[PDB]
Structure formats: C-alpha cells, structure tokens
RNA sequence: UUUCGGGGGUACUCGAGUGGCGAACGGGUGAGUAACACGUGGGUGAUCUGCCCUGCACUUUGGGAUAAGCCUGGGAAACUGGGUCUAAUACCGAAUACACCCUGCUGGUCGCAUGGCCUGGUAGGGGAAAGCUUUUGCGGUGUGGGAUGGGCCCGCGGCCUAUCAGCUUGUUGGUGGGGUGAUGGCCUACCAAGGCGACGACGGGUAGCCGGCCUGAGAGGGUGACCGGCCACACUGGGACUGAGAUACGGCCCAGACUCCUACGGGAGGCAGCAGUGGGGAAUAUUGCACAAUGGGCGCAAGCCUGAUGCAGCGACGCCGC
C-alpha cells in the first residue's frame, strides 16, 4: 500500500486468483462427476468422462494453474479407478 | 543465473578484486563457487590473472560475465577464444620487473670501488 | 548441419547406501522388525572404547525374521515415520 | 612518544655506559637521587628488569614496541636472545649510528626522522625501519653539505664500523651485506635475562 | 496555425493507465528455537528449479472483453458504483506436437527390495505459442541435456537439572483412498497393540548455531562483538493468495493492543532498512557525500533505480606508527 508497484500488484494478484480459482473449481467438478460415475458403476459413461476429465487436467497444467506432476497424479488415479471398477 | 563477478578484498583506498563464479543473487562478498582469477586495478599496468581452463569451462556452461569481467576476459583473450573470434592471444600487459636487489648491491660496490 | 534430436543423460554412479548388522528384539508390528545395532566409539576425553546400542525399525514384507535372530539391514527411503531400514537377509537364526 | 629527559641518570641507575662517552657517569657511577648510595636488596627480578631497561634505553625503544620485538624474536627459528638483539640492530637509526654519520643514537634518530636519508632510492623517515640484506642507504642532496653532516664526514674514527655495515663513499653511502650474528653484535648486555623476564 | 485566445498534426518524446519482469535478492535484528536449528559426512531407484547456456521441433487458426479515455452517481474522508468506449506480447476456444503426460500389453538388461534403465517395442487417449523492431536488432512455445539455486531423509558431534520416572492413543505399525514437486500418520477410514525410556524418555531452566575469537605448555576452560556461512523473526497472534521461488520488513485478509483522522456512518498507521527522536542505562555516532568504483533490478541499447556499497563526519573505543 506504500509502494506503487505493490499497489498495482494488489490488483493483478486478485485478477490471477479469480482465474485460477475458476479453473480449479472446473477441474474439481469434473473429477467429482467421474467419481460419481464410477460409484454408480456405469463403465460406458465413466470411460467417456475419464477422457474429458483427463484432457481438462492436462490443459490446466498448461495454463500453469496446477503443476504437471499434479496433473499426472490425478490422471493416474482416475485411470486406475476405471480399470479396477 | 550463474555469473562471473568481481568480489572486493583489500582495505580502504586499496581495492583488490578476486574473479569469482557466483550466483547473481549472492551478495558481493558472499560464498563463491570458484575463484578463477584476480584483478588489482591500483597497479600499473593493473594486475590481471585468469585461470583460462576454468574460464573456458564456466563460459561454456553459460556463466554470464559482468561488465568489468568482460573487459578483463577480452584483454586476456579468453573471451575471443570462447566465441571463436580472433584475438585469443590477448593484449595483456605485465609490469616491468624491477631490478634485482643483489645486482644493485654489486653495482654500488663497483661504483664506489 | 544438424545435431542429434536426443541427447543422452550423463552417467552418474548410483550412491552407496549404508548397511548394518543387528539382532531382532521385536516383531509385534505388521511387516516391521525392531533391530538393535551396536557401535564402538572412542570416548572424546577419556579415550576408553565405549559400546553403544541403537534401536532401528526395519521393513520386512513376509515376517521371515523372528525375535532373537541375527539379520542384515540396508538403509532405504522413509517407508513410514521411523522406518528407514529394510531387511536384506536373515543371516543366522536362533 | 620518545624519552627526552636526562640521559645520564638512566646509565647511572643501570650501572653501565649507554652512550659510552659520558663523563658524568664515570664521576658518579652510583644510581641517582638522595638514596642512590644506599644498599639495595638483591633480587632476580631486578636483575632481569635492568637488563631489559639497558636494551630499550640504549636503542631508544618504548616498552610497547620492544615487547613486539620480543614476540617476533621468540617466534623466529633461532635462539630468542640472538634474534631480539639483531632485530634491534636492524633499526635504521641504529644502522646510522653504527655507520658513524651520527654521534649518539639520539642524534641518529633525529636525523632519520627529519628526513635526511633514503633507502634503495626512496625517502624513509621511520626510525624503526628495519634494514634487510643488500639495502643501500644514501643521503639526500640538501643534507649532504649540511653543517653537522659535514662534521660527520671529517669526524670518522669515533667508533669502529661493524663488518656487516660498510661506508663506501665520501657521499657517506652505507651498504648492508647481511644481518649481524650475535658475534658481530657488540652490546654491553646479557640478553638471556630479557628472555627470562618475558617468560615470567 | 492564428485573432493570440487558443486550436490541430507528428510521434522524437512522455504524465496517468493496461501488460511483462523485478519486488522472495540486497539491508536489519537475535525475540523464539535444546530442534535435522546448526556443524560434519552421506542418501534421493522419493524430488522441484524463473532468468542463463547448448541440441531438436515448432511458432497454424479464430474469438469475446476491459483498464485508460468520455458522461454521470454515492461518500466528510479513505475510496467506490453505473453507463458508453478502445488496444495488446492482457484473456479465451480449436488444430498441429507424437520428444512429453496417463493407461493396457509385452521384450532385453542393471541392481539395492520398492524398483531403475534401454527417449525399448506397441495399442488407446491427451497436452503449446506472440509478436515487436529496422536496428550491435530483440522476442514466443514444447521438449532433450547442462549449469545454478533449492526441498526432503539419515549417521555422527556440541548446555544445566531426577528435590523431573514413567510418557504416548494419529500414538506405534499395516492395507484401501486423499494430499505433495517428492518420500512419509503428512491427512483420512478401517484393522493390529504397539512405540519411546536410567545409553535419562517425559518435564523444568537457560540459549540462535558455526567458521572463529580470548586464554592456556598442551589438554582443557571460557566465549560467538566485527568480518564470513547457515537458521529464525519482521507491532502481537492466526491465515492463505500471487509466483519458478514467499517468516512475503517498506504486500494482502482477520482478530488484539496502541497512535492518529472523522461530518460518528467510517477511515488510516507499523524504523529488529539508513539517518534521526523520546525512553531505559555505567555506556555506544551524522535527520553527511556519491552512484566515480564493485555487486544487484529492469531495458536491444543510451539509460534509469540502488541508505547494497564506496567514501566522508563524530568518540584515544582499539591496534600500529611518529
Ligand atoms: Mg495419488
Ligand atoms: Mg603508542
Ligand atoms: Mg509513461
Ligand atoms: Mg527477505
Ligand atoms: Mg499470454
Ligand atoms: Mg498410498
Ligand atoms: Mg533468547
Ligand atoms: Mg595449565
Ligand atoms: Mg502458486
Ligand atoms: Mg519498516
Ligand atoms: Mg515486499
Ligand atoms: Mg536505526
Ligand atoms: Mg538515561
Ligand atoms: Mg554496475
Ligand atoms: Mg554498454
Ligand atoms: Mg529513489
């Protein structure tokens, strides 16, 4: 609040938080939908939504919102869940 | 970035510098990765020594010289060599070695006798 | 003129993990044994050789080492809190 | 600082010639003051102390600087007493006195301090400057015709010149072939007592 | 261009603003901490790393906004709303990538058990980009290697106190999930009943640690000012956000104490940066001068910024010389 650059950064940090929050929410909804599909037991729906969720995880790592290793962990867990169930 | 810097040694009004490889963020008089040379500007010609084998390695891996260190690397020919440009022999000047003390003692002996 | 599209990594020698020998004092946890290691150090001031004992928790998958047995161990990454050793070989059963 | 008080009273207390040309000493070889005649109780500490006082009040070195000389001598690889004596002998005011260009070590100090000598072509006015092997000591042009220095030219003979020194010219040019060994040094003092004093 | 009140154009230039990078370094202090904090030696087949260096591939294609501007509202102030409008290397969708990420099958090989390697082979699915400049021209994206900077784990080492003997129930271990860059009760559900302790557990007291320094014949004792390396904190306590990276000193949010402003509705602060003031005390300095040198940030560069720093002022405070 004292330094000009910091005052500007207040505005810019907020803009980025909103962008990241929105993306993370979308990812979380997608993973939730897949989980519900697997707990319902519907191999077909579950497989279709695994592929869309997986690509969404990858794209979130491209925007820098999540780390690539975190995307790999999420993708791996989902795919293993579909193979087991 | 890893850089080639001058670190200040010596006392007041007598700046003596070691040529060191150090991370940009490290404070001037901080821990260095290597000492590859020294530079004494108060002399005439200013004293310059560089370990050319290490300077070539560090420039090879991408160490970025500071402005004065780049001037020194050109005097020594280590810059021209690293790039491939000519002038690798360099134009390093060395202080004329003063007369030996024993010879001046013999001179005084002969002169007076 | 063109360089290679793949650059292979330089060879690094794989490090030396520590090893030890001890005796099993406990096997009451699942897949874990407690092993006592013995060390001999010279006392800093008095110079007498002093014998000291350190308990260690080691991982064994199959429960092949029971209480009282002599076993060899090797360091490993953390497998849980405490556990940092794996059982290599049950060396002399008793 | 310097000691600038009476010079005879110091030799009288110590019972030995320091300047060595002093008539008032030979007239009254006893210590000074009212009680200078009286009997003094013997002690080893007084003997050791007075040998140190003879050294430092001969060469004109303050106790602080003299103690640094001791530590260097003891640090040096030779035997401490020899090293200490030849260090004090290396002093430029002493070298000037041994060369003969001065009458007293006090006069030698003043001359060196006032800027009348050069060593290897560079002016030196530091009396404690320690000469080294193959030093050449010369006189600046202005001081060559200087009236007391003229006296010094034609007063050669007061004392003998030691072998490590050599005056080679009428310019009064001094050469130092080496540092003096204990045999070369000739001083009215038992150096072993000073080494013992500082081991207390 | 003039009438001389002003009014246009240019973009050399540049206030405010959008955007990028920096602001996590550098500087301070030693409150807390008896701990993998520190020192020394290892481990990572359990990992991250902006900018820099050096291979390979590429840099296709569309879109919707908004700050600034202009009109206007609310408020004492701090600030803030609505409308209209504009641009990008700001933001967003798709193609391509098959080096890379995920999954199934399968071959060889090296070990140190998980495993590692052969960018192994193979099938299926998926992951980017940005332009500017006309000049020593600078940039953008993925990916291989390097360099640098880290993270985490472990052996050994350095205080007093049993007039401190038992402590512990996520606590010790296991499996299925979650979480992280990564391993791991790190988290969580269930299951087993373990784990640490007179080789002083759990308590209490004190304390940042070290290279070193002082003393000493040495062994030892004492100590950690300056200088140099780590750590910790930034009015007190808690929290996360942005980012390659955060104890975020001159960032943000909340609660508390204190100071200040107010129109009483509500606002605004944080010298353990440099200098300086009050206070406490036996006692410790100038509200200097420069970026000329060295180091750092941004910029293609000229350059700009730098109380880092280089120097100056004051005190026999110390050492040395005269
Ligand atoms: Mg997982
Ligand atoms: Mg003095
Ligand atoms: Mg501007
Ligand atoms: Mg900081
Ligand atoms: Mg962009
Ligand atoms: Mg797991
Ligand atoms: Mg404390
Ligand atoms: Mg003793
Ligand atoms: Mg982040
Ligand atoms: Mg502040
Ligand atoms: Mg900040
Ligand atoms: Mg201050
Ligand atoms: Mg007071
Ligand atoms: Mg500079
Ligand atoms: Mg330039
Ligand atoms: Mg400024």
Image (tube, grey):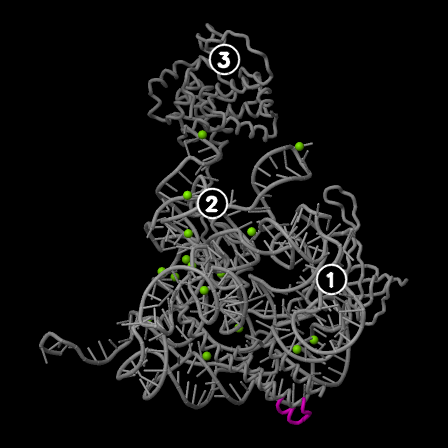
Where residue D91 sits in the image (x, y, percent)? 48, 25
Where residue A14 sits in the image (x, y, percent)? 45, 76
Residue position marked by numbered label 2 in the rendering = B10
Question: Cβ–Cβ below 8 Å for labels 3 and 1?
Answer: no
Give the Cα separation between the discs numbered 1 and 2.
Answer: 45 Å
Residue E110 lies in quadrant: bottom right
* Residue C59 painted magenta: no
- In which quadrant will I find the N terminus of chain D? top left
Q: Find numbered disc 1 in the image and state the secondary structure of the residue it sits on.
A: loop
Q: Find numbered disc 2 in the image and state the secondary structure of the residue it sits on.
A: strand
How crowded pointer 1 is (Cα within 10 Å; few <14, some 14-19, many 20+) is rated as few
Q: Find numbered disc 3 in the image and state the secondary structure of the residue it sits on.
A: helix
Label 2 CB-ligand 14 distance < 8 A: no
Q: Quadrant of ligand 6?
A: bottom right
Which contiguous range is marked in magenta?
A: A39-50
Whether callout 1 and callout 2 share a subunit is answered no
Camera sees residue B81: no
């Amino acid at each position: 609040a004292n330094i000009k650059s910091q005052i500007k950064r207040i505005r810019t940090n907020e803009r980025r938080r909103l962008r990241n929050q929105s993306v993370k929410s979308s990812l979380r909804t997608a993973i939730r939908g897949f989980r519900e599909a697997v707990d319902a037991g519907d191999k077909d729906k579950a497989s279709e939504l695994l592929h869309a969720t997986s690509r969404k995880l990858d794209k979130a790592a491209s925007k820098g919102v999540i780390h690539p290793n975190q995307a790999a962990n999420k993708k791996s867990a989902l795919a293993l869940a579909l193979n087991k169930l | 970035a890893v850089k080639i810097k001058l670190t200040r040694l010596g006392k007041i009004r007598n700046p003596q510098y070691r040529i060191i490889v150090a991370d940009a963020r490290t404070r001037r008089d901080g821990r260095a990765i290597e000492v590859i040379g020294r530079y004494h500007p108060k002399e005439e010609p200013s004293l310059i020594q560089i370990d050319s084998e290490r300077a070539q390695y560090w420039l090879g891996v991408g160490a970025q010289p500071t402005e004065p260190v780049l001037a020194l690397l050109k005097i020594t020919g280590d810059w021209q060599k690293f790039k491939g440009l000519p002038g690798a022999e360099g134009t390093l000047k060395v202080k004329e070695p003063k007369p030996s003390k024993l010879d001046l003692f013999n001179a005084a002996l002969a002169e007076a006798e | 003129q063109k360089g290679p599209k793949y650059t292979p990594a330089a060879e690094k020698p794989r490090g030396r993990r520590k090893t030890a020998i001890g005796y099993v004092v406990s096997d009451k946890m699942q897949k874990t044994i407690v092993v006592e290691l013995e060390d001999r150090k010279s006392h800093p001031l008095y110079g007498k050789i002093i014998r000291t004992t350190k308990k260690v928790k080691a991982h064994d998958e199959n429960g092949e080492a029971g209480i009282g047995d002599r076993v060899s161990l090797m360091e490993t990454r953390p497998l849980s809190a405490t556990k940092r050793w794996r059982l290599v070989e049950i060396l002399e059963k008793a | 600082a310097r000691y600038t008080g009476p010079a005879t009273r110091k030799s009288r207390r110590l019972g030995v010639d320091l300047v060595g040309g002093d008539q008032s000493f030979e007239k009254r070889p006893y210590p000074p003051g009212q009680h200078g005649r009286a009997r003094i109780k013997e002690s080893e500490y007084r003997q050791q102390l007075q040998e140190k006082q003879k050294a430092r009040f001969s060469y004109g070195v303050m106790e602080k600087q003299f103690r640094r000389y001791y530590e260097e001598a003891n640090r040096q690889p030779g035997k401490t007493g020899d090293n200490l004596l030849r260090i004090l002998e290396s002093r430029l005011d002493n070298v000037v006195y041994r060369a003969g260009l001065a009458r007293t070590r006090r006069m030698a100090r003043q001359l060196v301090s006032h800027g009348h000598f050069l060593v290897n072509g560079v002016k030196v006015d530091i009396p404690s400057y320690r000469v080294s092997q193959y030093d050449i000591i010369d006189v600046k042009e202005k001081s060559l015709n200087t009236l007391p220095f003229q006296i010094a030219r034609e007063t050669a003979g007061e004392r003998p010149i030691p072998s490590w020194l050599q005056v080679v010219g009428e310019r009064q040019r001094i050469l130092v072939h080496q540092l003096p060994e204990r045999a070369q040094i000739d001083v009215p003092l038992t150096e072993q007592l000073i080494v013992e004093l500082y081991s207390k």
